[PDB]
Amino acid sequence: MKKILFDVDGVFLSEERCFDVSALTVYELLMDKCYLGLHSHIDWETLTDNDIQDIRNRIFQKDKILNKLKSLGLNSNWDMLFIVFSIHLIDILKKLSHDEIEAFMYQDEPVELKLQNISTNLADCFNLNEQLPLQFLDNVKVGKNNIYAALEEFATTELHVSDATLFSLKGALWTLAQEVYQEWYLGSKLYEDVEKKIARTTFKTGYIYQEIILRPVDEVKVLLNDLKGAGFELGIATGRPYTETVVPFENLGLLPYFEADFIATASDVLEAENMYPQARPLGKPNPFSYIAALYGNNRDKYESYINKQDNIVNKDDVFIVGDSLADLLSAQKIGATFIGTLTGLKGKDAAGELEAHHADYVINHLGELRGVLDNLLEHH
């Protein structure tokens, strides 16, 4: 009867690795002889947590580039790594003759292979200048669509051309960069099964298995266990797709504490939208996934999860544990008790918005969750 719905990022795991893979993507697209092959580089198959950190640091410049893209509306890692890599590409292309440019920009061969024919035409040694992308966003209007427009105008004026559709969103180049990231993340094996494409490498194991933990698993395995011991039913609602949720939890040993029928993911919202397109977006602000994680995750009940959301549960029967504000509104929506965590990307600085939104409780991290359950009224 009593259920407690959990969110994944900002609670159990963080999103850092995404920014890591995003960095490694740009870097691999720059040094590997499979693409540009600008300069030498460490063997990908032997990278360490420090190498990756250094790479990320160089590419994003202490995350300055990474945080600027956020403030402008670019929160998708695929989009971020794409824009950052285009700025450097355009930079390298302005060193070749106009003829060489039109070649790479208009040749019938795939960009992936056309990238392999640029380094040989470099007169002098090219210098990276990893500050360019940041000095690119300087004057750019907020908004993904707007960001892509600036990137296109920049390419035309810099490369003295008029097309620049190669840099278009979801373009051939965008597809390349995005495939490189997915293999980096899911790993070759999971890449083929999820993306339905043949893997480029055979050494990428997938950083999905080396996800950044927020709280020691051995400690949460006891918390979850006791939670069940107190008659609590557990549930999961995340913005992560199916695999990015199951695989990590599986490898970590947390999955056994969550019934597969009570784990709602971005795949479900995606599926639900295809069945009921005019049902607007069923994204995280919409309590749909939380509702699916509560009553059960079966296609045949989706419609009800969409039409019946206003105060469908009592305050003492459901406890939503998350860090985002979008989860807070989903709880106030369905009538569930909300308990916010301070383990989000913003850290504890997110406490002000949580209290200004009347969050039932606010905890520092998943561990301090016992205090709330043993002091529901005391700490009310």
Image (spheres, rainbow, N blue to C red):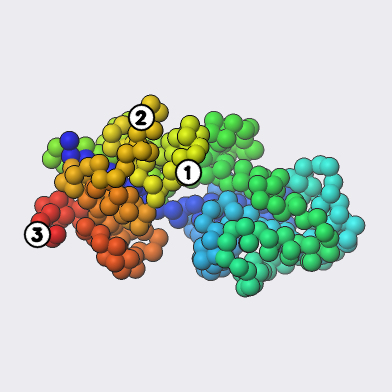
Residue 225 or residue 328, whichever sits in front: 328
The location of residue 107, given as percent across then percent down, is: 85, 46
Dot 2, how many residues are within 10 Å of its Cα: few (below 14), some (14-19), or many (20+)? some
Q: How many marks?
A: 3
**The residue under label 2 is which amino acid type?**
Lys
Residue 112 or residue 371, whichever sits in front: 371
Q: Quadrant of residue 121?
A: bottom right
Q: Earlier in the sequence, mark 1 or mark 2?
A: 1
Residue at mark 1: 280
Q: Evaluate if marks 1 and 3 touch, with contact meaning CB atoms under 8 Å apart.
A: no
Position of residue 139 relative to residue 225, above or below, is: below
Q: Earlier in the sequence, mark 3 or mark 2?
A: 2
**The residue under label 1 is which amino acid type?**
Arg
What residue is drawn where x is 57% and y is 61%?
143
Which of pointers 3 and 2 indicates the residue nearer the eye? 2
Q: Evaluate if marks 3 and 2 touch, with contact meaning CB atoms under 8 Å apart.
A: no
